[PDB]
Image (cartoon, rainbow over all chains, first blue to last red; front, side, top):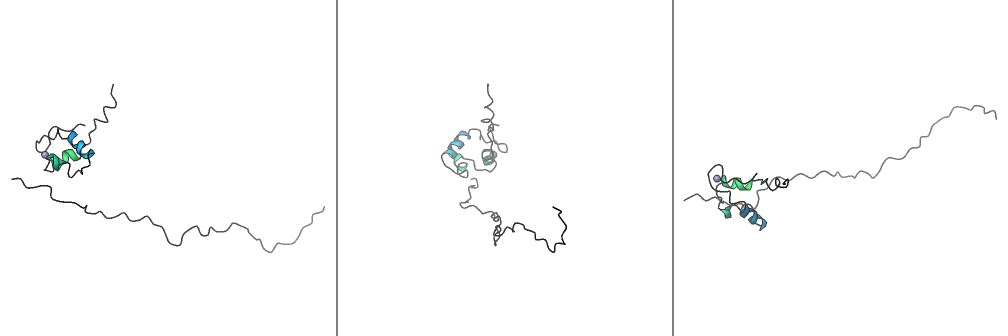
Length: 64
Length: 51
Ligand SMILES: [Zn+2]
């Protein structure tokens, strides 16, 4: 729905890396370089931000 | 106006439209094979061992 504040496996704050990851993919990085350059080195931390469907930009369209 | 009968007809010609020639090509046209997966270029170790 929204990015988790912590990675599930190890408790790294990955919840501050969603806007500054969209900003790197909009500025033409590959995803194999937009995750190393945010400091996500373990593949449990990369997993949280690579495979994330941010399903609240689709859910706020139904707003009063 | 009597309309008398006649003899037996020998043969019966059947007129029909011809077979569809030059419709199929002499070689066949298959769907091309989906390619085998490639190892992508630019793969390197991004994980360094800590400390
Ligand atoms: Zn982690």
